[PDB]
Image (cartoon, rainbow over all chains, first blue to last red; front, side):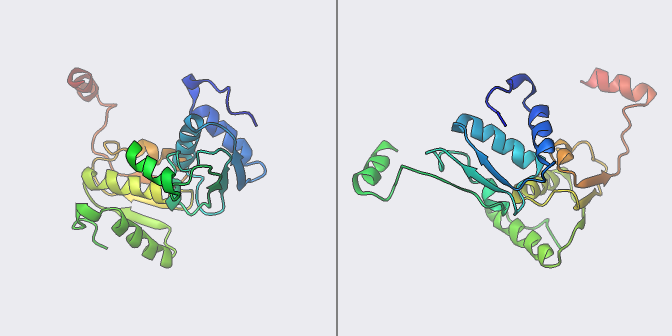
Length: 101
Length: 101
């Protein structure tokens, strides 16, 4: 299902209707494929509609896994996973991110 | 279980441990009996910890039912109820709430 083109004027009732139709298959495995400025919004709506108990298994398919406001679904028991090209543990990457900060 | 005296410095992990022991009881019916300052905080933690899907059922035993930030457990399907002495439908009350506002 497309989620990019939903207009901002009604971006509450749309995402409700969307997941309430995802209830047809009673779906619990999901992937979100969008840049983090969409991710933050749709994740906030997910937590607000309450569908982040354990069993939902959202995969974030972007290189900005920790860049999202991830640490709120963290505690819902819904498993979460993704992909990251940044590694804060590596040498000059680490020292740069220190410096950057 | 007391919820009034939990210190503000650590008022996140305590509320996890609290409800996680109710999860050891597998509890699904709950009552809160506290003023809004406690209500809003613990309700926020409830939604953040992911225990407000349908099946949970909360009674807010204070006279400030709509005064709380109730409108963000609204969509979780967890039933909610409370007790209200205020009635916006009343004759002079409505006109005062207009005036007040």
